[PDB]
Amino acid sequence: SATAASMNAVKDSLQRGQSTIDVALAAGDTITDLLGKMKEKALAASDTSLNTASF
Amino acid sequence: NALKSDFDSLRDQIEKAATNAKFNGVSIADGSTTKLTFLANSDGSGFTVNAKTI
Image (cartoon, rainbow over all chains, first blue to last red; front, side):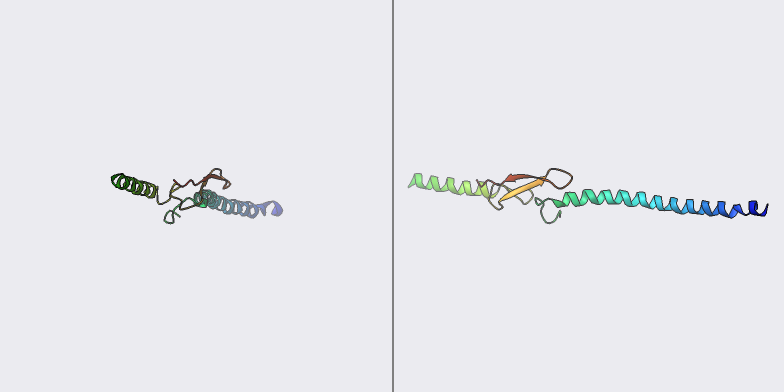
């Protein structure tokens, strides 16, 4: 029964790891959308036809 | 002399109409650059279009 009662620390530690990884996934979705926006921005700036101000 | 004056006026008109052909500070017909290249694909491939000086 002591070995069985020990497991609550395992459970709440796994929940804390779940919450940490969920925060990381939210930040990762944000950085992924930001990286795609820089994809489009550097692509729009890559061409030589632009004048200096738009560049 | 009158025909020469008309001819020189037409020549200056051609020079002005050619010099003024700009769009957003860049021109393909004035001879200011050898060619213009516009984007053609997401990897950066361009659409080359050679300049033609008029």
